[PDB]
Amino acid sequence: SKNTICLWYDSAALEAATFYAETFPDSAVLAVHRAPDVLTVEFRVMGIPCLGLNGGPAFRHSEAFSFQVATDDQAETDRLWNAIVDNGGEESACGWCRDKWGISWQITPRVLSEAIASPDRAAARRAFEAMMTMGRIDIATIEKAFK
Amino acid sequence: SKNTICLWYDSAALEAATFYAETFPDSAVLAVHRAPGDYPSGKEGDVLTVEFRVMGIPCLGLNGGPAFRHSEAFSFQVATDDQAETDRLWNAIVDNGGEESACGWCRDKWGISWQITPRVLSEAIASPDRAAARRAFEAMMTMGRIDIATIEKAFK
Amino acid sequence: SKNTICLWYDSAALEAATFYAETFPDSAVLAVHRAPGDVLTVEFRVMGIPCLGLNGGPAFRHSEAFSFQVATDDQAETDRLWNAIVDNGGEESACGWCRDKWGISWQITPRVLSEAIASPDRAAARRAFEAMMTMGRIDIATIEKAFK
Amino acid sequence: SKNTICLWYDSAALEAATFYAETFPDSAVLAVHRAPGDYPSGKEGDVLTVEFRVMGIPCLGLNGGPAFRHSEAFSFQVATDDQAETDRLWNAIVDNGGEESACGWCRDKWGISWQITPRVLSEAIASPDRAAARRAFEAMMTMGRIDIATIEKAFK
């Protein structure tokens, strides 16, 4: 791949990649590399080519980077949110959460993204306001607000 | 896209996306979304997000204000095909209010880490010739911008 | 994706994509598209490779001019993948080549065979090359014996 | 690579791979493998296969002789971001002993099908706005090389 997402881990790149592969569609562990014992892991997350580096604790993740996952319904939203949060993760605001390795994820319904970007400004703003009261996104509440 | 790389900016998402689009191959700004209401780091009508694509990767620039800062925990690794492309991309990132770092790593003006990494170097480091891979690794440790010729000599 | 592999189907792109996704690693059905006016195209991934399947009727037929060459790690994997393609209404061919139900050519090629044929030891490489030419499905142990 | 695109040539794999590498962006010839013995379409020491990469896709060119011929059953679809790249790539394939075809399709010197397909066109045809997608589709039907501006007008 021409451009690869490179993520820092403290001795857990393979564990993390394996978790992502079993949790999300079109995700897989591709290759494991030892130092010239795992130094790097090549992996895919919902199509995105990634490289995980086992480099110790020197660098910490922050919300400055996140994966934003577009979900199709409440069932998928809840499944992915719960998977990340319940596996040593944490809930945050407005569809944001964090995994066990400190990486930020947004589990963002397509309906929400569509609503906020809508040329109907009044409707978009109702959805935007409703979103700011939420942790996990509740699609029905977003749709009611938009309507 | 199912999974989009979201990067935090302090009121500079459109500027950054525009720079990436003129700098990297196969890159483009796709859509600008304005804030439907006032929020912590923007007024209604300000740029809230920008959709863009860099070399096959779907991205979103989010104008979230100064709350969060970037670090090397995240980086884009860009595979380059020769010295000319390596120099071009490195110079662009560094020269636009950016910073040089080590072993192909640099930083753009918004603090995002980029690795401009020759395919020659990546292939050398992951080689089944494990001593040769180490030699290349050790050579890389002496560089900021990667010199491909020097990596090839160390590997050989 | 900058460059996508586009494969022609006669009313079976989704069936084919789904079979590949179940059969091979890092493979998935990504999206299904109806005609602009049932399935017209399918986006899918096959061992990393981004693909597009087009449902365009019988006008075009596949041939050995195009094939996917799959690198396998042992006999168990070689047999698993060979059997999958051949047993699902497919066909066996020579030297690791086979054909799927939709007429697409696959090569199930042990890495050890690729390594052997490319070897700077010319005598060993040639023994492996000659052994390969007697085979349908590749037998790694026979290739290894010939190479040695 | 785990899965490699293998394309059949009549004693022309190296020439083809070299041409693709100088024509398309992010493309390269990687390795040349000579035949360890005589075979149906070559002598020992002739080029048997060539490893190459085209825009992210690992490929192998196989010198297998005239036994098989290419057709539109397989094609590479190359996404372009503007008219300049569209024209450059289309003309490169067609001019070097190739042929023009319909709706962004063309053929190279060795008979392999390429589609030079503006991202603007692909997005238009897959739009949930279905009537607009139809207009774009119908406009594409009137073209060989894709004119992006015309597609945009039809879509609108």
Image (cartoon, coloured by chain):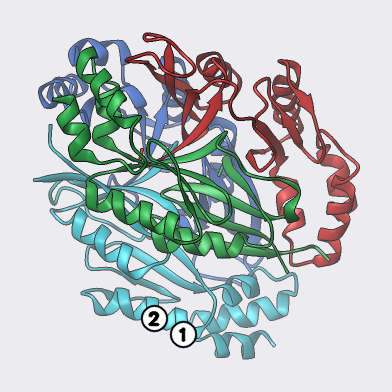
Chain colours: A cyan, B blue, C green, D red
Number of other residues with Cα within 10 Å of mark 1, as a class: few under 14, some 14 to 19, many 20 or more: few
Q: Which residue is mark 1?
A: A75
Q: Determine whether, in the image, residue B46 is placed left or right of residue C83.
A: right
Label 2: chain?
A: A
| Image location (x, y in percent) of residue D82 | 72, 35
**Residue A79: image tag:** 2
Q: Nearer the viewer, residue A87 or A25?
A: A25
- Where residue A95 sits, quadrant-wise, is bottom left
In this rendering, the count of numbered labels is: 2
Marks 1 and 2: in contact by CB < 8 Å? yes
Q: Quadrant of the N terminus of chain C?
A: top right
- Asked if C80 appears above or below B16 in the picture, the reply is below
Residue at the spot 65% in from the left edge and 32% down from the top edge: D70
Q: Residue furthest front?
A: C134
Label 1: chain?
A: A
The answer to whether one can see residue B130 in this image is yes
| Image location (x, y in percent) of residue D125 | 76, 56
- Asked if C110 appears above or below C77 in the picture, the reply is above
Q: Nearer the viewer, residue B93 or D42?
A: D42
